[PDB]
Length: 284
Ligand code: SF4
Ligand code: SF4
Ligand code: NA
Image (cartoon, rainbow, N blue to C red; front, side, top):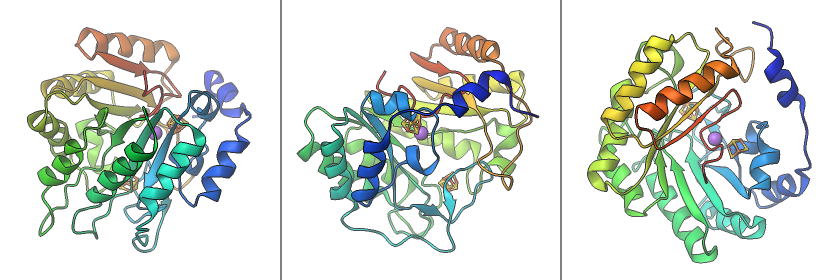
């Protein structure tokens, strides 16, 4: 499984990004871009986009693919996080913002209010900035606000796009994800369309975890059945030796081919390639 050529070059490239790095730390908030040293930073920062991580910076779930730092207990909730993010968005002059969060099984609203508050803070401070949500599944809802109502709170704030990743095919949901299921994640996407069919929905998979093309294609059809508009396909790269190994490096050609299959199946926006991530070119 050594690193293929098409990946060594872009994974070793560095760009001028220091102002952004400094501001994020200074304002006391966290981005996926920085928490994972994303190889797309030069391009995204250049396009005035970033992905902020709410309710962390650690997660307790420890999904075997995920780059978020593992935490011993739920991160204390910062009531000023929404305002601080909006201030960063303003000073960075971002045009397109993706909001995501860690899973918060411990909170009565599963953290859904934090999304709503952050969206409100950004709208009141930053004119023209669009906001995409990369949502948790909100599935652990016994005695909580229901999965449906968590989604509804966010849908009510009219994101530019509602993204919820399946991450992998049905067969691999067990080993790849913790606390998630295939049907629950598809239900997130369907629920958004029930609540407001005008909100674009998006999902994504990471390839290289042992899925086959046959299984990928079935998953694409499953996504179109719940009216998923947008798709990202990217290469799984283990964040550390403790994470799942890469089974396969999918070639640029294979990503192109699958990209085109997805377009034929009616996805209206598709990004497919080795360094593609959920937020990559999200602004379109
Ligand atoms: S791909 Fe996503 S995570 Fe990476 S730099 Fe762009 S916005 Fe940040
Ligand atoms: S995928 Fe979500 S739940 Fe799993 S570790 Fe990452 S942040 Fe936590
Ligand atoms: Na992302």
